[PDB]
Length: 54
Length: 71
Image (cartoon, rainbow over all chains, first blue to last red; front, top):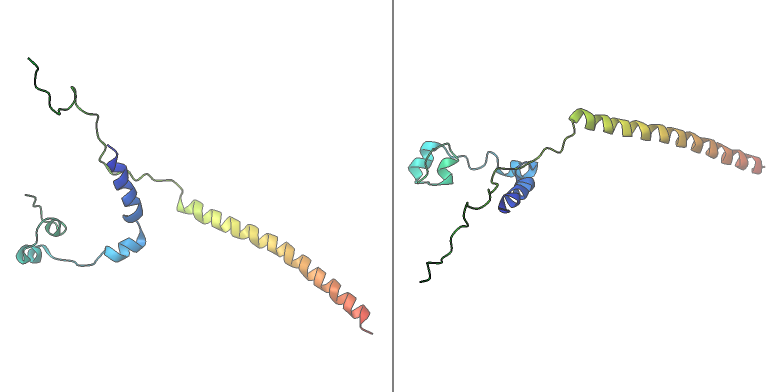
């Protein structure tokens, strides 16, 4: 019942920071077909829009 | 005799747990921030206007004294 505040602090540090966004946005873009073919799973699939969760 | 006793939740369950993202907006408009910046710039400009004019007068006075002492 106290962990959500920790996640919120992490987001305060990261989610809206311009340096973090410039470091992560548009980096390592993979298409859904390429992700499916290369054998990716989990977030690496769901980051490309694939709706799949075991 | 004794009934079973193992780790179980209390009757009625546990209290609700927060999981939604909580990123409150502190609150100040961009217009307001720009207005504050411009206002403090203008106040500094006026104060330094006055001080620099006074400094010009002081320098002129020092030059007057030097001119008087020169011969």
